[PDB]
Image: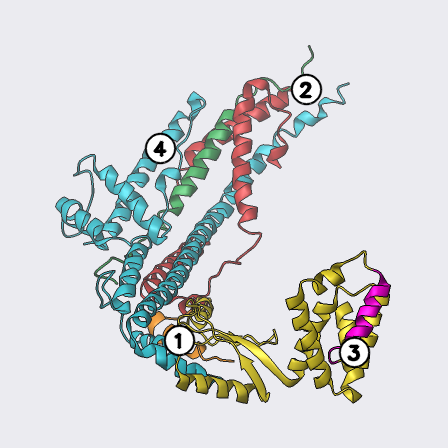
Chain colours: A green, B cyan, C red, D orange, E yellow
Amino acid sequence: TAAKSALSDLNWFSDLADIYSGQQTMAEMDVALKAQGEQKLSYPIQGKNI
Amino acid sequence: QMKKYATDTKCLDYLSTFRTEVEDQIANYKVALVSQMRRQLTERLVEKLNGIQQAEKLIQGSLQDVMIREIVSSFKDLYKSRPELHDAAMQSAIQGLSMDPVGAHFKASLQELAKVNLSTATADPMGTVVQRVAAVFQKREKEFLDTFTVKATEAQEIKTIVDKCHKGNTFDFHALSDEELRRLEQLYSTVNNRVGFETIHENSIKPVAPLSENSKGFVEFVNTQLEITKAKLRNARLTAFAHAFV
Amino acid sequence: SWMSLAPFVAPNNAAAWRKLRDGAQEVQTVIERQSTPGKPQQIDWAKWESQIAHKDILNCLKTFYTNQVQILDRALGALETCEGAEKGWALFDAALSACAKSVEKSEEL
Amino acid sequence: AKISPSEMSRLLEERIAGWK
Amino acid sequence: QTLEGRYASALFRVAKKKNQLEKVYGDLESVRNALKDSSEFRLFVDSPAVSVQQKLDVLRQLVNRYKFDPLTGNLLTTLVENKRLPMLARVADAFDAMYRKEKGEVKCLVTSAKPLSAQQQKEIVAALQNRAGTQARLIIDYAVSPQIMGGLVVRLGEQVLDFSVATRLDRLQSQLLAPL
């Protein structure tokens, strides 16, 4: 019943996961503010655009 | 033995490198996401054009098929009806033993067809081969355009019943609506998925899962702000969908 | 280098770590992929304008394409030059200090 | 590709000539 | 080329020179009619338990009764000694076809119903200028699938000139369903 990792109770693996997911999402939603300027669109519609 | 645990000093450099790396492995993520969107858009358009080309091809195939079938049936009628073609064919063969009415009638109908503008024509069993073939032409073209274009009834419905009833000068927001707004969203997913546009689905974003209490002060600032971005973006989407339809 | 931080994990802190690990894997599975071919798609309308007979809806579709690619390249070159994240980098720094406070304990020996 | 009335019909008309 | 073809080519290429084959042609036609009208001579060559003695005697005496030529007798003795006499009528018809083919062909021909003496004349003169064969003895027929346009076969096998309505029509239709 030995113990590797002479270091004591580690409890900072959760926070790393949380900040990783947070930075990932914050990037994902600082992207789509830019990639959806959406000036105008051109939809082909029967009777009018055709 | 303790010659083992000398590794346990190197559990501190790793975290410095964590902070140094993740602020770069992320800056090389937004770029890849942009290019992902570009790739998906391009592939969507390409598949659309392959489909539309194939449809055009099969249309013209069926067109010439019927163009031949109907001329042939017309000739099979006219021959058995008319007396003159018999002796004309006799003379034709006789002089050929050293033009026939079949090639003549075919060429005549083709020449009379080449300058018809089949769009201006009439119903299916309408006698004249042009009236027999243009029915197929127009009907097939209608069954074509409804699948790689939007229909004017779908437009009129929302344009006159849904969008402008919200608001005018800009068509601002959408909380002023019934639950049937969700159906409009479904309607969105039809149009762009027949035309072949690629718009970002905001809901592909996923919020954070809390793990421990110490993180609570961060996650909320994300998730709250995420809503402030998720709904906002929604508006900047649908206004476009409206301002094509006014 | 921080990916070689596995063996200092304990089974009470495993799934979280695994989540983190798989999270990063997702990112990397994107990036290399979206830089391996580079740009082989690059469609050329000279072909399709000819091969198609309508040339009435094709034009608007192409217009949409060229209107979106401009804004994509815009955002791309724009990001290629805060406070919302420091609230978590503080958690990271606290964890750093804790791990040093533990390694010093296990450097007595 | 090509259009039916003005092109294909002319082509097919050009195609039919043949005997012997 | 065949067996009966062998005897045919033999007697033809041997007899064309001196025999005045037309004489042989007439004698063989007489023999063919005697065959078709006897029913014992047919039996006789079928008659397998007959002595070759009686056969040879019959033939030698038949020389002195009807018209006869020497090469005819040589051939008859040949088909006797080679045990190939029942092939006699077949080789006779082979020789008839051979000689009349040297001189003039007989051809099949089809219409819908009765044509006219005028276009009949036109048909025969056109087929003659096409053949350039001075002798042509034809057939008339009525098959209405090829609607009325005159289809036929000038009898040499590799020329069935299909001047018809339905045939040109179907060939054209199946042609112009081609892609582009």
Q: Mark 1 belongs to which subunit?
A: E
Identify which residue, B129 or B50, lies in the foreground.
Answer: B129
Chain part drawn in magenta: E51-67
Disc 3: host chain = E
Q: Residue at x 61, y 73 (%)?
A: E157
The answer for how far apart the CA atoms under marks 1 and 4 are is 98 Å
Percent x, y for residue B79? 33, 72
User: Quick one: B135 or B106, which is closer to the camera?
Assistant: B106
Query: Disc 4 to disc 2, how far (Cα)?
Result: 43 Å
- The residue indicated by pointer 2 is C108
Numbered mark located on residue E64 in the image: 3
Q: CA distance from mark 3 to mark 2?
A: 149 Å
The answer to whether residue E62 is magenta is yes
Quadrant (top left/top right/bottom left/bottom right) for the C terminus of chain E:
bottom left
The residue under the point 71% across, 22% down is B5
Is residue C89 something one can see in this rendering? no
Give yes or no for residue B164 being in the magenta stretch.
Answer: no
The residue pinned by badge 4 equals: B223
Query: SS class of the residue under badge 2?
Result: loop
Quarter of the image with the N terminus of chain E is: bottom right
- As measured in the structure, the alpha-carbon distance from the residue carrying label 1 to the one carrying label 3 is 50 Å
Q: Nearer the viewer, mark 3 or mark 4?
A: 3
The kind of residue tagged 3 is: Asn
Nearest the eye: B67 or A22: B67
Label drawn at residue A5: none
Mark 4 secondary-structure assignment: helix
In 3D space, how far apart are the residues under numbered discs 2 and 1 (Cα atoms)?
A: 127 Å
Amino acid bearing label 4: Asn
Nearer to us of marks 2 and 1 is 1
